[PDB]
Image (tube, rainbow, N blue to C red; front, side, top):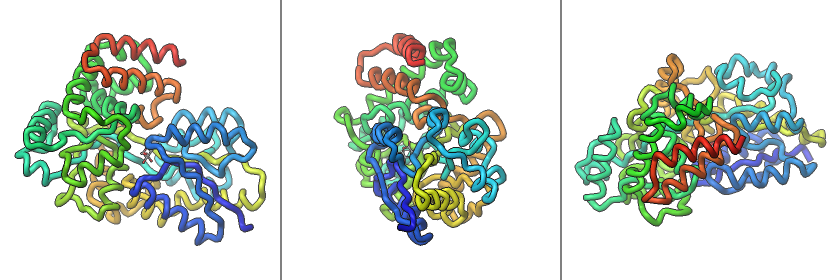
Length: 396
Ligand SMILES: OC[C@H]1O[C@@H](O)[C@H](O)[C@@H](O)[C@@H]1O
């Protein structure tokens, strides 16, 4: 046995699978065995359940898709391996933005390797559906509702949305970023500031979320994010509020920007970039050949060729800084420009819904408040903000 790579991840949709296939291929070309542990469940909760079993099993995966502050917990447990030598040889501190490199370190040592930078705060449009409905691509919340009114009148699903908590909170966080702005967003989700969490603007975010719910399919419970994307691709819906992993579904269907889809910053979030960094935390392994395979995985993750093909298929930006951005599609080039702009000011903000801003316990509290609210058409925004602050406090 040359050594086996076992990555625990949740890349299972048609688009996500095309991306992870590029990793499988490179590992095989490098002469190692690929043994997949893909665990289906958008946003990763199902994967995390499997991980919690496997991690203290004595047979951990080579790596697992573990993001944000949660990397600190796995590092604190002593389960991850330090990557000093591979990081030095492959110049990771030079290749990675400082903001990103810090997330990957436990007590100053790399313990995880990033593969991308997803943008969460996108809105996906089907321009052909917009043309049929006489609708205008929205740049403001008011325009978003105007477009939704027209799509509805035209007999389309205005907003294709799946009723799962992480999806609900993806929409909610877009609203918070839009209404509060990036500094307010940071105060609420990173600093967990009580006055922000319970303020009039957060209250208005909940009122806006409730209205948005009136423009979704009432029987959307359980609908996977790729199902929602398909409604837009197939011309049944006008819009989807989702990160740029949605682009992977458009690309996998052979669709092109302008003609088939557009993406625009979520209305009112122009200038802000809510980032989601997929990273592979590397577990301490026992088997010598599997350690060699793991070291190969760590090398591959930031190789220029892999950074290109993975991210072309995945819908995200590459995380490596020296890349020829002209090799990506127009939407990814827009993402790059928007990242650069955001990074100059205070616009670059970690996604709460995608595990970058908070611990998982705090995220879970927020998810519960937001679905409970959106599940109840009669719910009150003033109560929601009190529950939001209270539940966050109890989760810590
Ligand atoms: O499953 C949908 C998306 O969930 C996000 O949390 C992950 O970071 C993405 O890689 C994935 O495509």
